[PDB]
Structure formats: structure tokens, C-alpha cells
Image (spheres, helix red, strand yellow):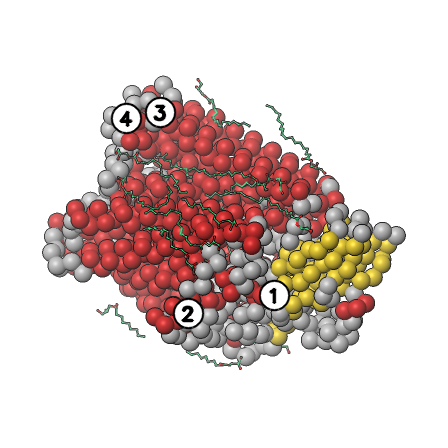
Amino acid sequence: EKPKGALAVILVLTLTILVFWLGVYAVFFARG
Amino acid sequence: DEHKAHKAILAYEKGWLAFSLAMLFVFIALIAYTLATHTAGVIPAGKLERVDPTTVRQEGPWADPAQAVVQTGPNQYTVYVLAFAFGYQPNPIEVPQGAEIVFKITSPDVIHGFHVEGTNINVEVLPGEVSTVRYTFKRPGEYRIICNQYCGLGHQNMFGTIVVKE
Amino acid sequence: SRVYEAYPEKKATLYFLVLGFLALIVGSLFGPFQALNYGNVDAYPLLKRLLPFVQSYYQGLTLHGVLNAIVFTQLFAQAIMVYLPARELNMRPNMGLMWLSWWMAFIGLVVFALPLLANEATVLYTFYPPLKGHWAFYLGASVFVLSTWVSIYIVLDLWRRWKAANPGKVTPLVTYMAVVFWLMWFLASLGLVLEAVLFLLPWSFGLVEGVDPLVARTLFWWTGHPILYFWLLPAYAIIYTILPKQAGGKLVSDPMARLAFLLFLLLSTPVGFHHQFADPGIDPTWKMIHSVLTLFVAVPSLMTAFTVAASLEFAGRLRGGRGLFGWIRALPWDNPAFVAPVLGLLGFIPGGAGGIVNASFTLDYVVHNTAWVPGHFHLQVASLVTLTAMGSLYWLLPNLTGKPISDAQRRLGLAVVWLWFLGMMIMAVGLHWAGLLNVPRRAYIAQVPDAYPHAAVPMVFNVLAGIVLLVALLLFIYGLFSVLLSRERKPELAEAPLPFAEVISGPEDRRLVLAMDRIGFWFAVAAILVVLAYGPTLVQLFGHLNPVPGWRLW
Ligand code: HAS
Ligand code: HEM
Ligand SMILES: CCCCCCCC/C=C\CCCCCCCC(=O)OC[C@H](O)CO
Ligand SMILES: CCCCCCCC/C=C\CCCCCCCC(=O)OC[C@H](O)CO
Ligand code: CUA
Ligand SMILES: [O-][O-]
Ligand SMILES: [Cu+2]
């Protein structure tokens, strides 16, 4: 049917990437 | 079952690979934006500017720390900073707020970092070369310079100061 | 043992592993001390009583870097990416060469160790000029690294011999991994070889007064990035081709695994300027290009995350797990060989997230040279790589020695693996956070105890990780020596097959596998991209060399 577990894993990975990236990018501008 | 699982896995992987590529492309676009704004001044001028680290303290713009701040524009100052073991000259560096500051940093001895706490200024300082970066200080007060490149036993205690006047 | 008469490759592999692990243990001793340092606690006077040759925090940090990140990881790479293709093809490696590779490593290490231990090369594992180490450090490091060239020849040998016996057949999976891996490494290595031969060696020998710091850093990071993948890929070979079996399942796609590896061959070297975002005299347009390519080199691991995840799910579904969480509990959580790499993969999520931030050019000015970097890479190498290596003790050691793993030793393996994992997670929080507070890396901060008051909270995580990791390490030392020096031997374990996974059913893309198999073509492409990504900058730098005198500041 569909690999729901894999998707869940790459979901956590995407969110972690996004929080880290957007987090740092906010920081960059605050210090800009 | 196995045959189906494999088709389903591969099909969703392709979706994921496309999404991941997109996200990465967006970041590329969000970085290109930073390149277009004033915040990019902290990126080093990638132009080579050789100097002699053995005479840099005797002759040239780094020889007299009290004259290291030069007005080079209507609203621009250039600072000739020397990062050395284990300190920075001048100490303090004194610049006006709202003015564009072109830091020209070099080293007499080994490599040092020039990391201005509270700001995006973060540049390796190499002996024999001049590091050029730009920043406009928007808030007045006292900013600490940290050396973030190992430079020997005096590394952890190597600090400097920037005073940004109103 | 007559098993070593028929498979002498086992004995050589063994020697690579043990020397690797010995180097890990010695390097790791400085770790808890460095962790307590970033927790603003000074336990160095204690360390100097136990180890009186240690003159400073920075000598310790040097040994820690060289021994953990250079020596162990290379010895593990040479162990894994020689022996695994050897078993998959069922062929003998050139045994004269394999032994020559070991001695080179051992000799190179000893010679480098001497100045390191005598405080004559406190330069760090990056040894940036003008900090000037003893010639024996550069020479010993060089001979140690060049050992890999002999490894490269070995696998290319095995591969060519197989292709002759088997024309019209595609390269087997593990061998395909190893071939692209070693050819990737050859291109990557040239940066440091050039740096040692042209600059560092003659300079340390007295033959030249100075070295140009910019060119050295530029040549260093030519090798410096792909070396990170050089550490990573051996763990990946296991994660892809062995871990699925250990987990109770199969590898879901052979072609995807090949694609990841092929991407690494292509994209691992032309990216070094991402270690040079804060360097002068390197044009920004070039930094942007490298940044983009670095983001690309993230694709093979994003791909890996899915292929591996799906393989783990498949295994958990086979073992009866239902829903979207149940496949996780269904996995063999009592088996340290399964647990160690899976935990390492977990921590790799924030690890790779921090890498993607670092690669982002301007965003790097935020974290460059702060505690963040160490926080980032302990997730990558000190966790995922190290853990996968620890977990192989439980299958590889018995395959190489015939020595059994008792229930007790297995339970101790679990404890070690968890505590190491959790210690690394805790330290990661402390270092990323402190990094965001502008705490510098490579610093004896505990000796400036009022310098970073804002870091008080992340500092408590650092102390915690320090003590947790010390215990993990002590348990690892005890556990490793308990298996290596165990009395009983059972030669039927040494003659058992490696737990290589099967590939799940379903037609692959034959065309893609064949395309990927055109290895000479991909090697040339890889080489071209390096000429395009480094040629212009390096031509400019070599035209404008400015060598400066060296310093010893320790
Ligand atoms: C072996 C170790 C290494 C890996 C791999 C690694 C990967 C990355 N790095 Fe890095 N890093 C940088 C960027 C990257 C990028 C973009 C990635 C990427 O390749 C990462 C991509 C990975 C992912 C996108 C993660 C995918 C996750 C997976 C595959 C796990 C999934 C979980 C599963 C499947 C399990 C779930 C199962 C269940 C049961 C639930 C840059 C800059 O652009 C710098 C310099 C920063 C500065 O300013 O100095 C840097 C510096 C370092 C240094 C310091 C060098 C020094 O001493 O100065 C080291 C040692 C290091 C190591 C390593 N690095 N890195
Ligand atoms: C018992 C576990 C260990 C602990 C507690 C730990 C602790 C530390 C900390 C706190 C630092 C930063 C020190 C500083 O920036 O001044 C560091 C540096 C380092 N560690 Fe470890 N570490 C451990 C094991 C390992 C392992 C297994 C590796 C990878 C194989 C390793 C690779 C690195 C490298 C490459 C450096 C950077 C050295 C440099 O900047 O010159 N660590 N570690
Ligand atoms: C399927 C849908 C396709 C559409 C998907 C589109 C992706 C949208 C994401 C980001 C937008 C980028 C916005 C760039 C503007 C950045 C401005 C900023 O961040 O400002 C900083 C600061 O205020 C200045 O001084
Ligand atoms: C799990 C991870 C936890 C995440 C926690 C992250 C906390 C740090 C966030 C942002 C730092 C932003 C840096 C900006 C510093 C501003 C301070 C300032 O203004 O100081 C200098 C000024 O000159 C005084 O006069
Ligand atoms: Cu100057 Cu560290
Ligand atoms: O560099 O990862
Ligand atoms: Cu890199």
C-alpha cells in the first residue's frame, strides 16, 4: 500500500531541517 | 506483497526526492537573497591583498593603532585591525553608529579569528593577507571581539573590544 | 588456526580493526575532559596526574582529533571497504599489498605519535600554517594517509580480476560501493598530498622559510571535505548491505543504494570552500557555487534516509509490527549490532540538519568556529560512524576470530551503545546551544570561567555528557578487552557467512544499473568537476603566493 513508517521518518527529518535552517536564518538577520 | 512493497517504496521515494530537492532549491534562493542585501557585507572581499607580516607593525596602516580609523566616505570608516598573539589593536576600536565600517584585518604571527559578538562579523585572519569585511553597527555600545581560531596557548584569553558611539 | 591459512584477509582486517579501536580508546580519553571544559569545569589538573606527558588542553585536543577522527576512522574504512568486497566476490585480496598497507599505517602512526606525545606538534588535526609542527608529525601523517593508496589498488585489483572472470556482468553491490568509494578517495586525497609534498614537508624539513596560509587551507579542504564522506561511507556500506539482515528484513533497492554512492563519487570533492566561507582572497561567486554543490552532496544522504528507513520498516513489518509505530518495536532491539547503527542514524537527523545550515554560505557566519561545529560533527562521526563500528564488534569480531559473544557481553554492548548515543545527544544540545551563544570551538574555556556567563545552561548539559561518556568509554574499554582476551575459540564462527542482506523482489532499472556501472566514465566526470570547481581559484593563488614564517606558540 504505502510505506507510512519511512514517511514518518523523513517527516521528522524535514521538520528538524526546517527548524534548524529557519532558526539560523532568523539569527543571521537579527545580527545583520 | 514484496513486489507491491517495492513498487510502493520506490514510488514514494521519488516523491520524497522531489520534495527534498525543492526544499534545497528554496534554501539556495533564500541564500541568494542574503547576497543581495546589506547583510552580505560580512562576506570577505575575495580579493587578494598581500602584505608582509614581519614589517606590518613597523611600516604601513597597522603600525600606528591610534590612527587605524580613517574616514574613507561621507558615511564610511575604514579600520586597520591587527589580530596578533594574543590581542587586537586598536583596543578599543572606536566607530560611530550608523556608519559603514570596512574592517581590514591582518596578522603578524599566526591565524586568528575575528568574531564580533552580537554580529555576523566572523572572519579568519591570515598572516600575509588582508581580510576585508563590512558592517554597519545599528545599536551603540560595547561589542566583544572573540578569537575563534586556535592560535596557541593564549587562545582562550584572546579578546578585543569595539566601542560603537552614538 | 587453519582458517587464517585459507582466509589470511581475516587476520589483516583484524589488525586494522584493533589498531583502529586502540587509537579510538586513547583519543577518546581526552573527550570527557574536553566535555567538562565546555561545561566550565577544569579537570585537567587531574588528567595531568594520570597522564604526565600532557602539557596542555591543546596537546590533548590534538591527540583527540588525530587519533579519533583521522586514525581510527581510516583504519575502520580500510578494514571495512577492503574485507567486505573481498567476501562478496569470494576472492583473495593481494595479501602482500594488504600487509604493506597495514605496516605503512602502523609505521606512519608511530612516527607521528612521537612528536605528538612529546608536545612537538600541538597544531590540531587541521595543522594550519603558520603554526609549525615537528617534521615527524607531517611525515608520519603522510605515510599513514598514503597507506590508503595501497587499499585503493587492492580493491581495483579485486574488481578488475572479477570483471575479467565475469564479462557482461554488472559489479556486485558491496564491490560497486567500494570501487566508487576508493576512486572518490583517490581524487579527494590529492589536495592533502599536494599540500604535504609541495608545502608542509619541505617547510618542516627547513627547505623553505614559509608557507602561504591561504593555499595550504585551500589544498587542505580539497581533501578535508571528502574525508568526512571517507569516514561515512564504510558505515553506509554496512547500513545498506548488512543492517537490513540484522534488522530482520532486506535491502529495498539495490539501484538506489548504487545511486547514493555514485552521487558521492561525483559530489564529495568539488565543495571544499564551505570550510572556507570566512577566508579572505577566495572570490564570493566561488563560495556560492560550492555552497550550491554542497547542498547537492546532501542529496545522497536524503536519499539514504528514505532507502534505509524503508528497509527498517520492511523488516519490522516482517517481524509483525503494525500501525506506524509498531514496526519500530518489532525490530531486534536486543541486538547491539542492530541497535548501534540505528541509534547513530537517529542522531544523524539533527547532525545533517546542522550540516545543511553550515553549507548555506552566509548562514555559516552565524556558527563558524563556534561550539556548534563540534556539536554538529559529533553527531556525524563520533556517533553514527563510531557507533556503527562498535556494533560491528558483535558480528565482525566473531567472523574474524571465531571468538564467541556471550549473553553478558551482548548486554554490556547494549549499555555501551545507548550510553554513548545518549551522551552524544546531550553533548550535542550543549554545544549547538553554546555555539549559538558565541562560544568558540577549540578553546580551554574553563580557564576563562567568567568569559561566557550566558552559556550557563548549555554548560550543564556539557558536564553531564562528559560524565555519561566517560562511563560509556570505561564500559567500552572493559567490554572490548573482555572479547579480545576471551579464552574460548570456535572456528565455525570464523567460517560462517557474513550477514549480508538480500535485495527485495521487484524489477530494478537495469538501464540505470548499467549506466552507473560505467565506472571509468564517472571517475572522469568526477575529476572534471574538481578541475572546474578548483582550477580557477588554485591557478590564481599559485600565481600570487605569499609564504610567511612559522610559529610555535605552545
Ligand atoms: C563523517 C562526518 C561528517 C559528515 C557526513 C558530515 C556531513 C555534512 N557536513 Fe560536516 N560540515 C559542513 C556541512 C556538511 C554537510 C552539508 C553535510 C551533509 O552531507 C549531511 C546530509 C545528511 C542528511 C540530510 C541527514 C540524513 C539522515 C539520515 C540518513 C538518517 C535517517 C534516520 C533513519 C533512516 C533511522 C530511522 C529509524 C528508526 C527506527 C525510526 C560544513 C559547511 O558547509 C562544515 C564547516 C562549518 C564551519 O563553519 O566550519 C562542516 C564541518 C564538519 C567538521 C569540522 C571540520 C573542522 O574540524 O573544521 C567535521 C569533522 C564534519 C564532519 C562530517 N560532516 N563536518
Ligand atoms: C567519549 C566521547 C567523546 C567526547 C566526550 C568528545 C568531546 C569532544 C568535545 C567537547 C570537543 C570540542 C573541544 C574543543 O572544541 O575545544 C571534541 C573535539 C573533537 N572531537 Fe571529540 N569527543 C568524543 C569522542 C570523539 C570521537 C569518537 C570522534 C570521532 C571519531 C571525535 C572527533 C572530534 C574531532 C575531530 C574534534 C575536533 C578537534 C579540533 O577542533 O581540532 N570525538 N570532542
Ligand atoms: C508549490 C508552490 C510553489 C511556491 C513555493 C515558493 C517558495 C516560498 C518560500 C520562500 C519565499 C522567499 C521569500 C524571500 C524574501 C526574504 C525576505 C526576508 O527574509 O527578509 C529579511 C529582512 O527583513 C531583510 O532586511
Ligand atoms: C536546543 C537549543 C536551544 C536554542 C537556544 C538559542 C539561544 C540563542 C538565540 C539567539 C542568539 C542571537 C544572538 C544575538 C545577540 C544579541 C545580544 C546583544 O545585543 O549583545 C551585544 C550588544 O552590543 C550589547 O550592547
Ligand atoms: Cu588568536 Cu585564537
Ligand atoms: O564537512 O562535513
Ligand atoms: Cu565539509
For the residues marked 3 and 4, what is the alpha-carbon distance in whole angstroms? Answer: 8 Å
Q: Which residue is mark 4?
A: C321
Q: CA distance from mark 1 to mark 2?
A: 22 Å
Residue at 46% in and 67% down: C57
**Amino acid type, residue under disc 1 in the picture:** Met
Foreground disc of the pair 3, 2: 2
Residue ID for mark 3: C324
Quadrant of res C171: top left
Please give left or right for residue B25 compared with residue C257 in the image.
Answer: right
Nearer-the-camera pick, C444 or C206: C444
Name the element at disc 4: loop
Relative to B76, residue C171 above or below: above
Type of amino acid at the residue the image marks with label 4: Gly
Q: Secondary structure at mark 2?
A: helix
* Residue labelled with disc 2: C45
* Mark 1: few/some/many CA within 10 Å (<14, 14-19, 20+): many
- Mark 1 Cβ and ligand 5 under 8 Å apart: yes
Which residue type carries mark 3? Leu
Label at residue B158? 1
Q: Nearer the viewer, mark 3 or mark 1?
A: 1
User: Please, which chain is the residue tagged with disc 2 on?
Assistant: C
Disc 3 within 8 angstroms of ligand 1 (CB): no
Q: CA distance from mark 3 to mark 1?
A: 53 Å
